[PDB]
Length: 176
Image (cartoon, rainbow, N blue to C red; front, side):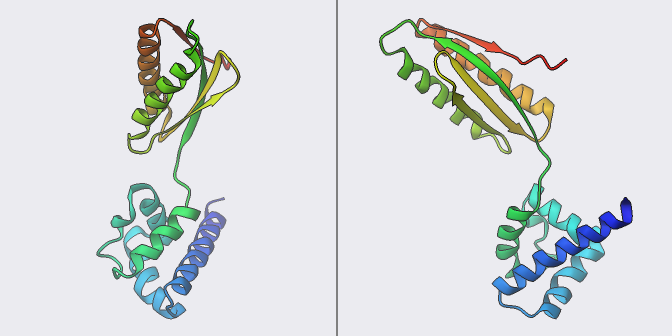
């Protein structure tokens, strides 16, 4: 439970810091003195400090540890420290009665995906499953945000498809 979980988090924080020390070419004691001690005093747990950095940016540590550490800590924390997320998936059935309907569909999807993906922390992806099915996968901080992204994307796709004389439909997987 709790304590063991504290052990495992501290173990991992130690391996990560050691990796950083090596990359940055610094002795282990220095890493402890300069990084471990400061972060532990203020976040109460070094791994939690690494999680904040992973979620809210490496600058959360700026000021608490020398600057030379930030670069290497970012790369390492970003690779190994998970950030809470949810992913949902749905699919569109899109028909565009035109010799070039297919390419028009990609254009619309590509445009919708890119737009949606410029939003911080959101990651949208489309998977063509063979006409007229297009699966959509969304990753976001929480379910509310992910649903809002879907709704936004669906509104744009339907609008654009009905403009090109086609027809789009959003299907949702009923889970229970």
